[PDB]
Image: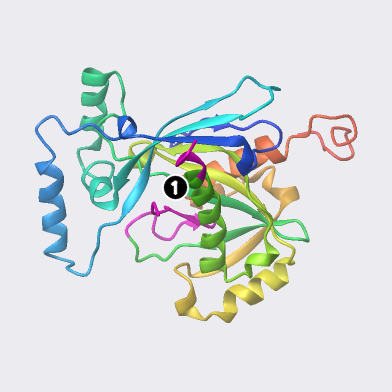
Amino acid sequence: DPEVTLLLQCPGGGLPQEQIQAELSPAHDRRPLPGGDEAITAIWETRLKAQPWLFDAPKFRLHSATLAPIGSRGPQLLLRLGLTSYRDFLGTNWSSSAAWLRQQGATDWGDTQAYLADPLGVGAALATADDFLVFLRRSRQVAEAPGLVDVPGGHPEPQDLAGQLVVHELFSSVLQEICDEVNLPLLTLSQPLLLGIARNETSAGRASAEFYVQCSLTSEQVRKHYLSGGPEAHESTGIFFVETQNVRRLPETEMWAELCPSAKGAIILYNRVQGSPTGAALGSPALLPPL
C-alpha cells in the first residue's frame, strides 16, 4: 500500500493519555519557502476570491514522535509538535507543486517535510459492544477523497507544562469528533488508546494519530443514533459495520480499494496493535485461524 506509511506503532496494546508527553515549540514549525511565503498567500487569495465564505483555522503540526525503550517505566512517548494552519496546508501539501517542495526540503534541510504544513489529523478504530468496527461513506461532492470509505476523525484546532494540555486536547478531540459525526452520547465511550501514527503519501506525507475507542452500544444502537440526527447532523452520507473477525483480512477484500489512506492506516494499526495476539490462549489455532 504505497499511499500509507507507518511512522509509529505503539506498545502494550496502545498508550493511554497519562503516558504521553508533548513538546510544542516554534522549532517544530514549517520552514519559510525558498522564494518566500508569498506563494501561499497568492493561492489563498485566489481561493477566497472564488469562495469568500471560507475561513482559516490553526492546526497542530507533526514534526516527529520518539518512543521510549520498550518495557521502561515512566513516560513512553514524546510528540514534537509545531503550529500550522488550513491556509498553509492549501499552499503546500495540497499544491500541485508539493513533490517539488519535498525535493527542495531534502536538498536544503535533509528533511522531505521541511517546507510542508503537515497538519496532524486524528482517527479512530471505534468498536461496538457486539464486536464490529464503525465505517462512514464520504460524499462524492467534497474535495478530498470523494466517495471513499473513512473512519471517524478530524483535524484538531489548538485551544510538559503546556505539553499536558496539548495531549489532553488531542485525546478529547477524537471523542468530540465521534460525538459530532456519529451522534453518540459521550458517556458510552471509553478513554482512547493511541495505536500509532500513519502518513498519507497522496497528501505529501501529512500524518494522523490513530486511536482505539470502545463503545458500550451495539451496532444496531450506534446506527439508530447516527440516523436520528437527520441528513444535516453528519458530513458523511452513510454508516456501516464490519465484524472485528473480518477486519483481520480487510486488505484482501474489494472494500480495501475504496478506503481513504488515513482510514487504511487506522485499520493496519488496529490489526497490528489490538489484533495480533502474543500469548498462548489467543494464539491457539481455534482462536487464531491459520491464513
Q: Which residue is mark 1?
A: 121
Q: Residue at x 55, y 50 (%)?
A: 171
What is the x, y in percent for residue 154?
45, 55
Residue 145 part of the magenta segment: yes
> For residue 134, which quarter of the picture?
bottom right
Identify whether 150 is placed above or below 79: below
Q: Amino acid at mark 1?
A: Gly
What is the x, y in percent for residue 215?
70, 60
Identify whether 248 is placed above or below 242: above
Q: Is residue 23 left or right of residue 241?
A: left
> For residue 284, which quarter of the picture?
top right
* Residue nearest the viewer, comparing 138 with 66: 66
Judge whether residue 257 can be spotted in this image.
no
Q: How many marks?
A: 1
Q: Residue at x 34, y 32 (%)?
A: 28
Judge whether residue 82 can be spotted in this image.
yes
Residue 160 part of the magenta segment: yes
Q: Which residue range is magenta in the image? A: 143-164
In terms of secondary structure, what is the magenta stretch mainly?
Answer: loop
Q: Secondary structure at mark 1?
A: strand
What is the x, y in percent for residue 245?
75, 49
* Residue nearest the viewer, comparing 27 with 142: 27
> For residue 24, which quarter of the picture?
top left
Q: Residue at x 9, y 43 (%)?
A: 38
Seen as rendered, the residue at the extreme front is: 161
Q: Is residue 176 left or right of residue 95?
A: right
Q: How is the image coloured?
A: rainbow
What is the x, y in percent for residue 71?
71, 22
Q: Which quarter of the image is occupied by the C terminus? A: top right
Identify whether 167 is placed above or below 136: above
Q: Residue at x 63, y 50 (%)?
A: 192
Q: Tell me the crowding category of disc 1: few under 14, some 14 to 19, or many 20 or more residues within 10 angstroms, Cα based.
A: many
